Image: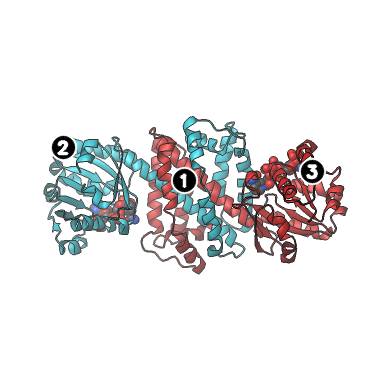
Chain colours: A red, B cyan
Amino acid sequence: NQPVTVIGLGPMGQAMAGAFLAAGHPVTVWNRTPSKADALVAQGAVRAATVAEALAASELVVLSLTDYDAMYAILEPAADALAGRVLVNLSSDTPERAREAAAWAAEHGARYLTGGVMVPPPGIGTPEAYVFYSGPREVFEAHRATLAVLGGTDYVGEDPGLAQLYYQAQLDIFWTTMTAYLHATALVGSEGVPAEEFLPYATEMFDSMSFLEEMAEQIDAGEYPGDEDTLAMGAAGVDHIVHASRDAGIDTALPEAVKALFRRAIAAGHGEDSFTSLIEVLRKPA
Amino acid sequence: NQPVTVIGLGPMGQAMAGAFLAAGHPVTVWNRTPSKADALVAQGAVRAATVAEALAASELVVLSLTDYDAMYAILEPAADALAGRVLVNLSSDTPERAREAAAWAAEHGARYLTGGVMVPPPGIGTPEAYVFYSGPREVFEAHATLAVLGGTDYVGEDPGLAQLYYQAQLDIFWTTMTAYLHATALVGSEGVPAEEFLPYATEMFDSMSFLEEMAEQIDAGEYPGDEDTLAMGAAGVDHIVHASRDAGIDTALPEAVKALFRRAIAAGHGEDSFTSLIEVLRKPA
Ligand SMILES: NC(=O)c1ccc[n+]([C@@H]2O[C@H](COP(=O)([O-])OP(=O)(O)OC[C@H]3O[C@@H](n4cnc5c(N)ncnc54)[C@H](OP(=O)(O)O)[C@@H]3O)[C@@H](O)[C@H]2O)c1
Ligand SMILES: NC(=O)c1ccc[n+]([C@@H]2O[C@H](COP(=O)([O-])OP(=O)(O)OC[C@H]3O[C@@H](n4cnc5c(N)ncnc54)[C@H](OP(=O)(O)O)[C@@H]3O)[C@@H](O)[C@H]2O)c1
């Protein structure tokens, strides 16, 4: 009961359009590569010939593109067709690029919402699916239901860049943690321990991290009471990891980066504070 | 019952000695700072007057010291008393330093078990604690007393293995903690409290349920890159670097991740699964 346009027919976009179509929403679609639409048009989507047609076809225009450079390459030549439309950009990019695009959309008559999808293309439309949303609350509340088709709707604030900040911070946890798991698996692997043999121990390590609330409370108070886990303690242990990694013939760049941050914080006088104090150097460029 | 000596009465050694004592073992203790044994001695522990008498008091000698340098400083002047003893070094150090110490102990007639303790001092004695052990399987099998401290997790004969497993677990711990704090600082740049983002970060960690598929890929050495290629990850890491830069936060951690992705792409893995990054992590630059 709401027309929807989907610019961007990549794995993600195709999934969104299909979910919109399977929810019964009128769906118009466009893509630099039309062949990517043959499937949805066969399922009942309208392949627009131009970007202008797609934009006019619906007020709600959801964008799933590689990056914002792609958006501007698509939409700028049709910028005079953006008036009245609501652009919901779900493409990954920087917060600042989102705040710049929001201003660009405004000057061209369009409203702008930023979105960060937290599921793979296949996950779109499942209970585990949720999308960070930021921008004008009224515009969000006006199109929440339509967007819920794709997954949970999580409005995080008015700043257009906030949704992407949340997304980037989550991927910052993800990729860095994945690299740590691979580095540790390589370390034990240097003595012939299969990855599937270390997996139980790695898995239980992550289940042991049930104290993040305490750390978050420390950060939010700006107080890092030392007690059972000084930063100096972690610094000594990180040195053992660096030295073990070297001895084992594996890469040392990752543990060395962690070590240098600990040294920064100790030089700043947090050695006796809780290791949460490390955030104080993480927030300050060296 | 079965005597046990504990050398090193810092927070961990004090907790280990207490556990042995509460479990009914005869316990002899030694520490460079003797005041730290007072509370234990008041409960039945024997304060050895000399390191060598501590070694002689029990065949099983548990060491809980800062590093292996502390061990040699303590034990070398008394190396002739190591004969017949079983040294169980629960001190954190490198796998190579463990192998070296095992050879030194054998030169003095002592057997050697390496241990890696995966709980803080308050965690000793819970059945939910565990300790990696490596060294002669017959020596580990003969020394029930160790279970007083927590689970006994024997990883093999190589004396370096227990510390290898331990350093790898701590590798995950500290790097993941650094990532959590950096990401928390990133959203905090715009005033999002850590306690508001934590629910989302917790979901992230609870969503890591594919590590098995990664484990099988590593063991096969096959990194089928179809769904999530390394190139796609690198592009995401670049946005993270740039967002961190724009936010005024330190970029060293994300730049370190970015450099590893670049190395893997330069090794031909751009279109492989992100697990292929292990091929650069297994080899120095
Ligand atoms: N799970 C996820 O994959 C996920 C999660 C969160 C966010 N995102 C964001 O959503 C995007 C889309 O998901 P994806 O990675 O599956 O697909 P993708 O490969 O990034 O496809 C992006 C889309 O952008 C289009 N495009 C790129 N450059 C263009 C240009 N110069 N002119 C016109 N169109 C251009 C592509 O058209 P063609 O099809 O013709 O190449 C394609 O439809 C991601 O790149 C990311 O930015 C994805
Ligand atoms: N959460 C934890 O505390 C924890 C958890 C798991 C593993 N570990 C590991 O277990 C070991 C024990 O740690 P801990 O918590 O007890 O604190 P610690 O400060 O590492 O232990 C200090 C102990 O080592 C002794 N020592 C240090 N340098 C010495 C030297 N040069 N000569 C003689 N004795 C020396 C101290 O003697 P004095 O007491 O006389 O000063 C004391 O008995 C460490 O290797 C640590 O990495 C700790």
Q: Image quadrant for the N terminus of chain A?
A: bottom right
Marks 2/1: CA–CA distance:
38 Å
Residue B125 x %, y %:
27, 55
Residue of label 3: A44
Q: Chain of mark 3?
A: A
In the image, residue A21 lies at what x, y percent? 75, 48
**Camera-side residue: B81 or A157?**
A157
Where in the figure is residue B275, as x and y percent of width and height?
53, 37
Q: Is mark 2 within 8 Å of ligand 2?
A: no
Disc 1 is placed on an element classified as helix
Which of labels 2 and 3 is toward the front? 3
- Nearer the viewer's eye, disc 2 or disc 1? 2
- Which chain is mark 2 on? B
Dots 2 and 3 on the same chain: no
Local packing at callout 3 (Cα closer than 10 Å; few below 14, some 14-19, many 20+) is some
Chain to which mark 1 belongs: A
- Give the spatial CA distance, label 2 vs label 3: 82 Å
The image quadrant where one finds ligand 2 is: bottom left
Q: Amino acid at mark 1?
A: Glu
- Residue A55 placed where, x, y %? 83, 51
- Residue drawn 56% across the image and 60% down it: B197
Q: Residue at x 22, y 61 (%)?
A: B36
Q: Residue furthest bottom?
A: A221
Q: Which residue is mark 2?
A: B109
In the picture of the structure, the residue carrying the numbered disc 1 is A256
Give how far apart the Cα atoms at labels 3 and 1 are. Answer: 55 Å
